[PDB]
Image: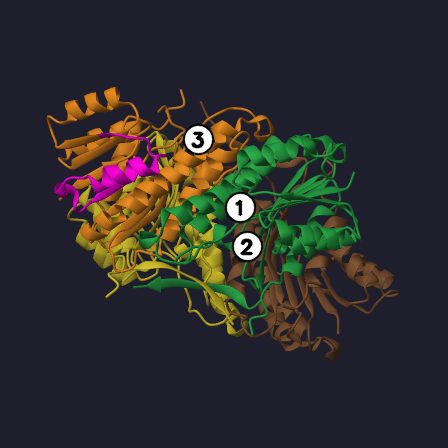
Chain colours: A orange, B yellow, C brown, D green
Amino acid sequence: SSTLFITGATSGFGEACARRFAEAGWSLVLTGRREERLQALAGELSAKTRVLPLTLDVRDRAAMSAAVDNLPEEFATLRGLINNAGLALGTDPAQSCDLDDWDTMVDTNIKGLLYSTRLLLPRLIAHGAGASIVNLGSVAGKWPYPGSHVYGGTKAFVEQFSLNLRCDLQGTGVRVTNLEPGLCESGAHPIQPEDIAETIFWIMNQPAHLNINSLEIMPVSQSWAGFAIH
Amino acid sequence: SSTLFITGATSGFGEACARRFAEAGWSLVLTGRREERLQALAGELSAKTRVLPLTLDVRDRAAMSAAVDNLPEEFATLRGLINNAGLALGTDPAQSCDLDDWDTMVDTNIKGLLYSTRLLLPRLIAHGAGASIVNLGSVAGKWPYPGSHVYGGTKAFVEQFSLNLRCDLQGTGVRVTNLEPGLCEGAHPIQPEDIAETIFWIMNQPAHLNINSLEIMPVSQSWAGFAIH
Amino acid sequence: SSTLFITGATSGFGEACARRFAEAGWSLVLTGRREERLQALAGELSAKTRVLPLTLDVRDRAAMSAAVDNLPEEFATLRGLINNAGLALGTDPAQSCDLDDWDTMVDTNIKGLLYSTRLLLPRLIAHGAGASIVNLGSVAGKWPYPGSHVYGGTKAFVEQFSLNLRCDLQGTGVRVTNLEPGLCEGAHPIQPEDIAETIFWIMNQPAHLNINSLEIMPVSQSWAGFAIHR
Amino acid sequence: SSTLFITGATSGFGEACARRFAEAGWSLVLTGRREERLQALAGELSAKTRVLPLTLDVRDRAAMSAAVDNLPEEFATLRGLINNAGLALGTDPAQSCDLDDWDTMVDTNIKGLLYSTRLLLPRLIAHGAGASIVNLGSVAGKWPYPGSHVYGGTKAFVEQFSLNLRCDLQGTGVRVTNLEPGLCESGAHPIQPEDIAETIFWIMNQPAHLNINSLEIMPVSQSWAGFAIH
């Protein structure tokens, strides 16, 4: 039916997405490491829609494959997938960074999204016309700045991956979108999680024949600084 | 007030946008080369909203500038500008092309856009918060293909100008968006009404949000990769 | 024969390129609006190599078309074209710019390069294997910043036009390169001689190779990231 | 101070680079999984320069770090690093790919690159003015195509990481270049590994004040096909 899988559903924009699509009565599968926060959200949203909470680390390939294999028949076809699970770690310039932080970002922001995408593609294919993948990219995937190193690289991966995935999805009906948000809260009036939630709702309800390849959104307060000279 | 200026309002996605924003009751200035067709649309939409048809070619700096000065006072402030006037003049190999055609495209797709945006900018700035410029770019602005030459060049101009313009508009509230459509009308291509819907959504964005760019293809359209000769 | 056409040979990186290719013994066609300055450079380099100075404005399609039609037989084939004529006219905010300035920039930076390329292309094609077009782009074609508006726009045109041109030139042997310099003449900025050297290397690439784009900045120059207005 | 560390050295652009720099007499650290092929190459080049072959998988973080900390005092400063280790594992549609291959490409092309660059970065900074890092990206990092999926994402990661790195290295003198090759030999007259080696040599021998941000190079026989409509 209208079924949606959201990774990191207590992380970043995941909760706001969960709330927005619950308001619309989509069936939800919500992924989260924090079992207690996830489960409370599921319980709350359970009053307006069907929710299946899965306590799960997207880095964990085996657990993710087990979770997907064990999905109820309700989800034999999947309408939506939001790849939201991701994080930025550290402050240091690249040369004094902790490789532990770099591993975690790569495993989460890239491998996590690859696992959730590959494992769920057959169900997205099976839905067909109107199916939608929304990947959480970032302005950091395009525009370099100090300290961005791996986080930006990670988001640049996501951007190209989305475009590339569309080249493999011929005749399938499945859409793919890279949403690239700028400065969030989540007097500058930053993007709010509910703004991301509304935008993804709009993206996923696009007429079956249309694919938004990419959409870069910033607060109007945010623009580009140009170059630094040392 | 909700006021909208549209270049090439008879030409591309211009009519669809005119119709779509009339439904929402925005007051419309519509420009076009084809006077009879421009006036028939204005006459038709005048039943739903205020419309001002302006017969002009966006390439003509003096005519555009005169027309802007002569706008009625309801437009002392301007909410939206859709820079939609633009054309492609074939996909011949560059080495065989006619420089007149290349002239027409530069003057229309770049200069026409520049004139409309600069002349109207102070009115958009006067409106402030909530104001939006939508430039019509194209997928041709970033993806090379045989025969793209000048059309694609002009659309990459539009893309970069859009982003650049935002760096100049700090503190004004004015928003700038580059909309980049792919294949339009078994492909189920993009319909003009889809672009009209998309622009309405961009222009109605909450004041604090700026959609920098939005690339849209029909789902049937993807990338072919590389050619080897 | 090693024949080279250089637009704006007394502007920007143009003189440095004429000198560099002069010492390598290529025959030069050099354009410039200022006749005396152009002929002095032509006179001087005449001791090292054959030089044809043409006094013309690249915006002038008719002048440009007549000059190319009147090229001596030495130039029945063209090895190299450097599209170097171009200028900026401020970093004044867009809303307050002079449309005269903006007109001048697109006529020069865009149409000038268009007329150049189109009128000479049959001669470059007649040369065939090893022929080279080098367009002067800029970091401005890619990275947005305050007051860049039209100049960056023009340089983005140049970038896309370069790549696009390649798609029409199959079977011809002709190469096209977009060179994108940053800060030029503490900071140790790019020197005109650095550009001459890099264009020399580009035009002498083995015939089977095409450098699509090459972005060069002084090492003192990087990216500042975003600006937020409060 | 003229030392070079090359990852994936035994057969690729890798071997070509080792051989090219050996002619110039740079002192070589060569990294490779294939011990015997690696040792034979070091033995051959020991006639021309100092070589140190290190048997290693760039994916293995503990081994890379143990290898780096165990380098002779000769490499207390490091002049150049070529991050060349990387692989594609086929062109099948994403929905039918094996996640093992995706792990392998992310671990090698991203993580491997990140380990060698973080671990050696303090040695590159110690050298300072004139030091160069050359990452091997690809046309795939920028241009989508069927079956590109993870490989292209991986190369988009490399490009953005390259540019981001420059923002962290202000004041050090260290240069970072993303090189983006197209169709290679591994009647189209494709890029030969010796061409890659030639271009990296030109990059690394650049005047100290200059940074080549990126250089995309295709065989002239290669261009863009545009769009597919299903």
Residue at the spot of label 1: C142
Q: Is residue B129 left or right of residue B192?
A: right
Work out whether residue C81 can be spotted. Answer: yes
Residue at the spot of label 3: A104
Q: Start and end of the magenta stretch? A: A54-82
Q: Is residue C55 above or below residue B206?
A: below
Q: Is residue A158 left or right of residue A226?
A: left
Task: Spot the residue most to the right.
Answer: C47
Would you call the spot at circle 3 few (<14 residues within 10 Å), some (14-19), or many (20 or more)?
some
- Picture quadrant where residue C54 is located: bottom right
From the image, which quarter does the N terminus of chain B lie in?
top left
Q: Amino acid at mark 1?
A: Lys
Q: Please say if the residues under marks 2 and 1 sit with CB atoms less than 8 Å apart.
A: yes
Residue D7: x and y in percent read: 61, 45
Work out whether residue D143 or residue D201 is closer to the camera in this orientation and state it. D201
Residue at the spot of label 2: C159
Measuring 78% from the left and 61% from the top, which residue is drawn there? C21
Chain of the residue under label 1? C
Secondary structure beneath label 2:
helix
Q: Please say if the residues under marks 2 and 3 sit with CB atoms less than 8 Å apart.
A: no
Work out whether residue C163 or residue C74 is closer to the camera in this orientation and state it. C163
Q: Please say if the residues under marks 1 and 3 sit with CB atoms less than 8 Å apart.
A: no
Q: Is residue A61 left or right of residue D209?
A: left
